[PDB]
Image (tube, coloured by chain):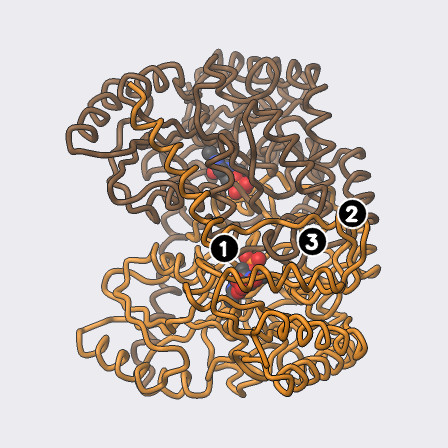
Chain colours: A brown, B orange
Amino acid sequence: GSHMRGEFYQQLTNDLETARAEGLFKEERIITSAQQADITVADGSHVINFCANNYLGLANHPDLIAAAKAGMDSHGFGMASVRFICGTQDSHKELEQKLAAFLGMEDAILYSSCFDANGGLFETLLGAEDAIISDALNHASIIDGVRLCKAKRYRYANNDMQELEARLKEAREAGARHVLIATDGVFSMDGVIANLKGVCDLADKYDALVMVDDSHAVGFVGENGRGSHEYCDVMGRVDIITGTLGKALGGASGGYTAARKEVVEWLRQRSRPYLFSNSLAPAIVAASIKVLEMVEAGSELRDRLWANARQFREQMSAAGFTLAGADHAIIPVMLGDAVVAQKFARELQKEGIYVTGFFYPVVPKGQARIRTQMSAAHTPEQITRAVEAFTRIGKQLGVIA
Amino acid sequence: GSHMRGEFYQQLTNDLETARAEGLFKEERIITSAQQADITVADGSHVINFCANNYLGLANHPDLIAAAKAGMDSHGFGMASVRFICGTQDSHKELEQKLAAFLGMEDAILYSSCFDANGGLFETLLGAEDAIISDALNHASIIDGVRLCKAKRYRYANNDMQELEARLKEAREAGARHVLIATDGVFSMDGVIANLKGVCDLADKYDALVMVDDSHAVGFVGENGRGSHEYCDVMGRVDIITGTLGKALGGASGGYTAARKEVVEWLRQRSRPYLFSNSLAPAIVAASIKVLEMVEAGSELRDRLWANARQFREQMSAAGFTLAGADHAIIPVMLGDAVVAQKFARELQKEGIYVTGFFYPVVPKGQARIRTQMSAAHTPEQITRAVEAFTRIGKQLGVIA
Ligand SMILES: CC(=O)[C@H](NCc1c(COP(=O)(O)O)cnc(C)c1O)C(=O)O
Ligand SMILES: CC(=O)[C@H](NCc1c(COP(=O)(O)O)cnc(C)c1O)C(=O)O
């Protein structure tokens, strides 16, 4: 019979139509240009993109494209193999060495994404006798990595050092052997930088390891763009740092875990995504080696980005919008209702501003928002223009007075 | 205090030392050339690679490199965004449409790897009231995808249709709502092709969905290279098919899930790796569109691959070796002892043959082997050389008489 399978398919169709009615259906907008500030969409119109992880504006940089091409010319198109078989080229090692040095760590191991780095981290290093204490606002990739781990789990309210301490005492009282605190370096839907000084101080007091996902920090957060550990001045106090090559560092693909030598080598020996998934492509490896140099010499880019973030926040703050977070390129405009968020975004596009509405499940129901993201590429003029558009539409939709 | 953190690092060091003592430490060998049959290693010497997923020899093909370059010239280096925000270009949709048509499915959704396509599949479609029945030999990526799902789990011995039916009865009698059978199309460490005819017939009898991971079949298995569903004559009967772009289809990176339109759209709306991980890079998207045309152009590469597989299996079997599986490019030479596998691999490189030893945890302890993989790029002479080297070393080591 096909009664149950028929139901499976019918409920999917029903649930999709229901999502649409509730303003929860994500529609993909086709972009026909390369990733940059000024993009072109399907109908050929030009709009300013204010929602990319292209923080330093390098996603379409000539130098990275050139490096990628040179990489394919000398090292090929694909490895067609996981690292331990025949997927390790000299350039993979050069990149890992360069990454470890950049982050101030002993070694680094490559993955095809930070989602995988996180997924293949916890289960490999901790077990049933251990405990993991996570910030409740942690990224989905951290949560899923922790779900695959046998360690006892505990959670503390976002940036709440009082609860973190309570959970640490709880874990230790329960007899946990090794304890690890896991937190985003920057909470991506809120534009909030973690309180790593507070976290590390507690880690010392309770003998716990510290893991930080710096996907939305590496390359532009910190005076040398090293990440949240530099920004919070706890360099050397974070045991494990994971990151991505798909954000500020090029935006193509790839991720990694940087830590002490023992951790990294054990990950190479037992991390499932590393053992059972393709090695990073030569084009990405080559371009990533080049991007780290561009980042190290990107002080002017960071200055621009930082100036852009303060301009947009200051101006939107003056306009009366409710904005989450502080001191980061991610500036979420809080709207609550998903239908209003989608409408606001569509109206903004008519005004030449490209942003996306965020709603369940990427963010909680009732807490919909438009997460804007500044880039070093944006000009003061574009930002003023975006602000004037947000203000006009915000007033028309009853979002602001 | 720091007793526990100190112990954490010491134990990792102890674990590493214990691993190499038992012949379970994987050393990576640096390759300085592009991926191909005749590769170059660190010291500049040339060796023939018989352990790559480069089934059609396209990993360093000039047409793919050219397509990748053109893709970057028009679409940039990276998307620096997940698909629903600003990571969808016209080319992403084009590739998904081409993949769907190629596989004989309604639609397809791209991921950065098949590891993640599997990881983000099950949890999104099934829940606590459902059941997943898995072939015991399933790949780690399927297993980890199932581990994130709340559905009740059942396992059946590899290719055991009797036990598969037993579990289907068990699940249904237990009151399961939706039941899904999950299986590799080709089991990668053994070179065994799944019995999809038997699986699908049973799926109909018990009203169950069927999922197949065709990573080691898409592009070269089947008269038209469509995969195990074509080979087993069950095209259209497999509800969900996942695959990779990192094997026969180029070998760079990327994965996908193909299924009915409503399944695919629901995945776009709720699959975690899709919502919270970078969109596929333009270079890979472009090259992938080209590779599908290359696979379709004719049967020449597939013919050579199968002739090569036939030759190696016949010659190695006549030479006295114990081999696993049948009828596939993957031809495992069973050695049992990890120390012997490691030694055999090293001795083979001295003879100009590059293969790798496989042991715990990639395969059970006591079941070490050297998994060879034929490629359309291999020549009859290279294979004969390989067989002669294997024979010579095998006799020297006492693996064969
Ligand atoms: C290369 C191997 O040794 C082989 N590959 C992994 C694999 C995947 C993952 O593909 P991605 O690189 O993540 O796109 C998916 N399914 C299967 C069945 C396999 O084998 C392996 O694991 O042996
Ligand atoms: C692009 C977003 O909207 C943002 N990015 C994801 C993310 C990752 C995954 O990086 P990969 O693309 O897998 O290399 C890892 N950590 C964090 C903290 C985030 O946010 C997002 O999720 O909102």
Front residue of B351/A375: it is B351
The amino acid marked with disc number 2 is: Asp
**Label 2 close to label 3 by CB (< 8 Å):** no
Q: Which residue is mark 2?
A: B43
Q: Secondary structure at mark 3?
A: helix
Mark toward the start of the polypeptide (1 vs 3): 1
The amino acid marked with disc number 1 is: Gly
- For the point 34% across and 41% down, which residue is it? A126
- For the point 24% across and 41% down, which residue is it? A129
Tell me the subunit letter for badge 3.
B
- For the point 34% across and 82% down, which residue is it? A2
Q: Residues within 10 Å of mark 1 (few under 14, many from 20)?
A: some
Q: Residues within 10 Å of mark 3 (few under 14, many from 20)?
A: many
Q: Which residue is mark 3?
A: B284
In-image side of A58 versus A222 (left or right)? right
Q: Determine whether the beta carbon of the residue marked 3 sits less than 8 angstroms from the nearest atom of ligand 1.
A: no
Name the quadrant of the C terminus of chain B. Answer: bottom right
Front residue of B3/A162: it is B3
Tell me the subunit letter for badge 1.
B
User: Can the viewer see residue B349 in this picture?
Assistant: yes
Q: Which numbered disc, 1 or 3, marks the residue closer to the eye?
A: 1
Query: Where is residue B322 drawn, in percent x and y?
Result: 54, 80
Q: Which residue is mark 1?
A: B23
Query: Where is residue A28 drawn, in percent x and y?
Result: 56, 49
Q: Is residue B380 above or below residue A95?
A: below
In-image side of A254 versus B8 (left or right)? right
Quadrant of the rendered image holding ligand 1: bottom right
Front residue of B145/B136: it is B136
Query: Where is residue B215 drawn, in percent x and y?
Result: 56, 67
User: Can the viewer see residue B109 in this picture?
Assistant: no
Front residue of A178/B258: it is A178
